[PDB]
Image (tube, grey):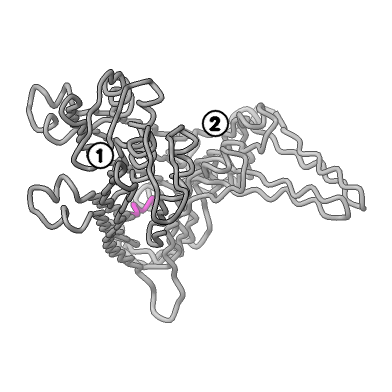
Amino acid sequence: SGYGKDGNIGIKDEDGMNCGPIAGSCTFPTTGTSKSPSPFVDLGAKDATSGIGIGFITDNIILDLQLSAMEKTGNGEIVSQPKVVTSDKETAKILKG
Amino acid sequence: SGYGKDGNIGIKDEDGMNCGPIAGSCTFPTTGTSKSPSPFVDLGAKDATSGIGIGFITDNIILDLQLSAMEKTGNGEIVSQPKVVTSDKETAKILKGSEVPYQEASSSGATSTSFKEAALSLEVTPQITPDNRIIVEVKVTKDAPDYQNMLNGVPPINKNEVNAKILVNDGETIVIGGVFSNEQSKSVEKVPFLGELPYLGRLFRRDTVTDRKNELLVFLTPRIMNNQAIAI
Amino acid sequence: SEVPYQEASSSGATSTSFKEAALSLEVTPQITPDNRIIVEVKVTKDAPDYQNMLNGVPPINKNEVNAKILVNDGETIVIGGVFSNEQSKSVEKVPFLGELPYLGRLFRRDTVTDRKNELLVFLTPRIMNNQAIAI
């Protein structure tokens, strides 16, 4: 699973199974899957966030590899200048708010 | 996904699948889709916001590319001038506005309906010198009734007020006080690789720039009524 | 009319504070021989608050000038005046279409509001001594 924009395909592969694909794996050497409707929908919604790179294989193996990156730059400049005319040795105030 | 007006077609492509199109993709090289009803409705409603550019392909590939831009300009000018006639070395006031109450109705001994008027107001204590000049202590407040008060929540009234004592001649106008607020805000949201490319970055850098500059200034001119009082 | 605020307060404080949104004059005139008066007058025009009519938090609206001035009997003066000039312009525009002149009216959303309210109070005192001498 990712962390900057957390993603783990396997959980949403279970959600894909909820969609209904046929997945069979009897041993670590032996596996096969067919009838997979999960990639296009699960990844399309899943990967909607800004920066994303998606790579998917299903027929030989189901391997979905996504890179999710966000780069944000914000610059804020505030210049406020209040002018008050005051008599000597007296208090005066300007207030705006 | 966009950011100024966030958009990501893929999520609403799942919503499109809810509409019912046939989408098949068994490998990254191999994909195909048919029976797509999602683009016209999903994009039409989705892209309703003001500035939008929509480009859609579905048969070869489904690629929807929309640019959503809003540009807003508002200029507000308020000029309010209150005139008060006051005797020399006396206090007088002009007030126009409304007094929001806070009923601190307090059962045990304290009933304090505190109430304060968001108003344009002048409180003046002028002292006249012979050469048609005045040294006056004036509190000048421009307070506008709080929205939250109109909202019946916790009411913060807005106050722009200068209190000071100054000397000016009768035929003279001065700046009692002034403030210029210059707000410069830039926010750009960008995917790194696409953001790099110049043409692509405008397509792939989400820029929000806001410039708000409000300046407030108060002038004043006192016209001696002695010119008439001597006649009186 | 005097809107009340019943701060009915159980423990020792019953303060039905009540204040009239009214047109009102409070005058303390001092007469000088040459048919002139220096008078301390508080002139208030207060209108009953909508929220008070709404039974919410009632902000009554007050336009009031309090001052002491000298004027002759046959004289009218401006006790006080205020002119409020509000100029508001808001234009909402798609950049490209907003650029084009004919298209921009079609594609620039303009809201312009100009509200200008001026309030002035005059005054003239007619000495009743003219009648009181007859009296």
Residue found 23% across the figure and 49% down from its top: B206
In this rendering, the answer to whether B37 lies above or below A48 is above
Q: Is residue A24 left or right of residue B74?
A: right
Magenta stretch containing residue C88, yes or no? no
Disc 2: CA contacts within 10 A as few (<14), some (14-19) or many (>=20):
few
The residue lying toward the viewer, choosing from B180 and A6, is A6
The residue lying toward the viewer, choosing from B115 and A30, is A30
In this rendering, the answer to whether C18 lies above or below B87 is above
Which residue position holds label 2?
C126
Which residue position holds label 1?
B72
Q: Which residues make up the magenta segment? A: B221-225
* Secondary structure mainly formed by the magenta segment: loop
- The local secondary structure at tag 2 comes to loop
Residue B179, located in which quarter of the rendered image? bottom left
For the residues tagged 1 and 2, is the chain the same? no
Pinpoint residue C10: horizontal percent, then vertical percent. 91, 48
Residue B219 visible in the shown view: no
- The local secondary structure at tag 1 comes to strand
Residue C95 visible in the shown view: yes
Disc 2 marks a residue whose amino acid type is: Arg
Q: Chain of mark 1?
A: B
Pinpoint residue B172: horizontal percent, then vertical percent. 26, 58
